[PDB]
Amino acid sequence: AVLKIISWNVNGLRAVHRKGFLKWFMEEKPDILCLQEIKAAPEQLPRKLRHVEGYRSFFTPAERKGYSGVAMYTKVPPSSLREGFGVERFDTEGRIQIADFDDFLLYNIYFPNGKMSEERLKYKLEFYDAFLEDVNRERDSGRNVIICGNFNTAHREIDLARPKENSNVSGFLPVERAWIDKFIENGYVDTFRMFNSDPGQYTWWSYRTRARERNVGWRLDYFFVNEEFKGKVKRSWILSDVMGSDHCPIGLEIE
Image (cartoon, rainbow, N blue to C red):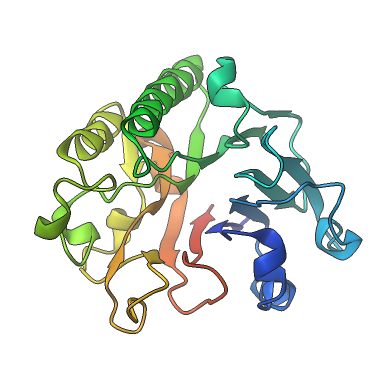
């Protein structure tokens, strides 16, 4: 069977709801939809966005009300989900959903933005290491893995419009970029670059200064799989023209 997964950093679920989310979700018909930055308390949500016909949903909020948070809709439920790495400084921020879909684990992860402070940058780089430990433990078990979400780092100079102007900015720091290399040489494939080696391919633009209109963006959202799984990947693409957030969606087709 062809399995379609979408990943979208919605930056406000009730915000994207006011900008055509449910209409879009209906016409896209993914098998699994992974959502980052819900910024909403799940039980205090219009029941029509928690309930979508054909889908089971799973919300993982931050303990801080209206901050961060992730979610997952799926036609087939997972056998269960894990909501953390087992390090509670990493597990209280609404950033982790690890769903067990038999053939594979799906990591739906909202990786921390390290721009606000030197401590948040430290948290981000530490978050990255807990994640790597976690994913390696599981594929070393024999588990196949799919990881999508807001990684919050552009990997190579090709992954943003202004590489040289951003070398001392979180999102393109040589240390953040090197972890992606480290993540990659640990046996994981950036699935987008399996099929598309072109520039101009971004998933995030700043709302201001007509950034989207001028394609001044960063490729911050990713689909990774473990090397052994990559022959199952049919498509890895970007939904550049879907509006409603400062991020666009990305897709994966697996067989």
